[PDB]
Image 1 (cartoon, rainbow over the protein chains, first blue to last red):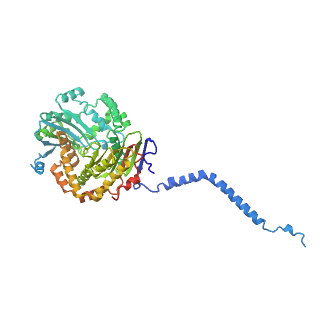
Image 2 (cartoon, rainbow over the protein chains, first blue to last red):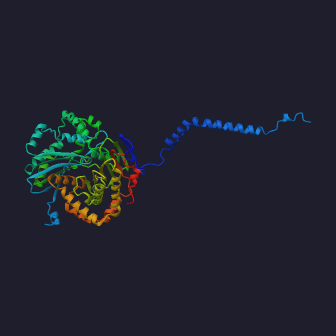
Image 3 (cartoon, chains in turn orange, purple):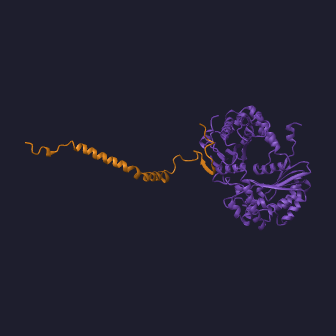
Length: 81
Length: 443
């Protein structure tokens, strides 16, 4: 339940922060944020996208194949009379 | 003899200015012993990135001899007359003073002038003190309380001059030149920025006479007699956390920006701090202490000690508190400490101030307990207020303070403000800035 104070044994680390009122909430959108969003996107697209692309294909095919098999095969009535 | 009468019958403080711009002030008593010294309006704040720690380096040579009299000679002369030579350098104020027999007030004044004007700055002594200072930095690095206050300034005034420490950097101390110290002295130790103060059994006119004789070197240009106004130091609500769980106790210091010397509100802040007071594990009073925070500290064993403060400067200051606690009681301490600050702004009582006022009076009277402490007041007063302020004036001001006044002033500098925080040691239990920031309102 109560954990702050007995978590880890830490030494020689200094940290510096500013009040939320001394700084901007969403700073450097163009020089930092977006560039990083792109970085992040890029480093993952070829990990994620591929299998989904394949799922999409299998879907396209299987769907088209199903409908194709609903169509009539003219070669079933060629010699019908 | 009533408190009032005793306050009015105190000898007045005489002031006279020389043509060179120096000011000579003193308070006369019937004491065979006295203290006299020169209070300079100089310090680390006047230094910059390249000469930080110069005024300190100088403070080390100011006693190792002058041109007229080398080291041994200088020391022997002072020692052999039973006089005491001390002094200090801070962020906005420096001082060199001597305790001696009123019978020597004149020879002393000569000595002082010789120190501030003709320091030998022995090329070889400089390299020698360079190593001494480096050892003093390692000694002070173990003084949590001072490491904590340095850090408090380092962040509260980050980016500015008050952010620097008085002793200076390791790189500066390793490379400060005989020329730099010299430059420092010539640039800052100047008549219009100095104050010859004295207290004890001394003739103001005899003091000012020896003063005229040794504090001469008048200035020609206008740039030499003008006291430079320093650029403002921006305050920043922020925190610096230096963690080392290997340290036995933790030090925490929280503070808001203060008004600055000249502001009258300071009398109220000092009354306010008087309500919260201070404490340490050897206050026999124990659980019956009037300071609520002190009482809680005892009942809940919140800390080893705590103290409030209202450090002033020309244009700004630090109003806050500092405590030392075991790693596991920091949170409750900070909780109660901030709680009390809220109480100040919101529910202060007439009783509370009645007491705080008395406490404050006896505190101001205590800072005038001897020739050196009184001399320090004079030096500081003229240097900060450009005039001495009697105990009777202070008492006049203190008397006007009431609960409502404490609340408004405290609400003014404390309520819903973004504090500056410095935490050193085993500080894991101290909650984040946002949590602390919330302790700044309502309670």
